[PDB]
Image (cartoon, each protein chain N blue to C red):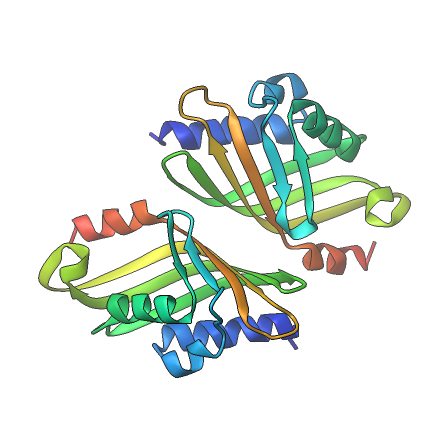
Length: 137
Length: 137
């Protein structure tokens, strides 16, 4: 019973968190922007975004976006929750360990309503909470 | 023991929600931006923003932002929560009545580290939930 724009957003998040790049790539064109505003990083276009997710998530054991609430205005979809990640810790400063983190965050997705491709994803992530958790591991 | 940027964010939200325009105007200058991304509305500068808030909140009986979680990376503060408003319903399509709503929203505030003034506020408000609440009013 969720609006179509919300079903689009869940499909996108399912592919991302399942590390399914064949499905995920269907949502991207050359002009898609993946922007983490909190980290001031941007990845642009199918090839660069996919390549970044491959490097980031290689070997990850668990990755989910636990959604507390979502809503939309037209093709802008807003999702509030937390990301949990479990995996080898090299890339988080913790070699030889499996890290486990639960990061509060807000993600927006804006789709082009005529192509159903992503125009912009914006992440706002609570990196201090991540740092605090990693210091104890 | 919150960082200074989160303290600024709380002072600003305190002034905004109390309708204390003298206190609130201390955060603004010629270039400050208020953007409601979910409403496609933008107001720039002290004069325009205060004029907009004064119009908007005229005769409002109760107003608050019940913050569930807040975090920041440097000058950018993210606040997740719920906006409660009780007041005249003309702007909300309920003329001659008092409406009472509780709206999930995410607000970001970016402050200038040199001056402590607001550079940009961005709102993401769940307007469909508002509309569903107004059905019974």
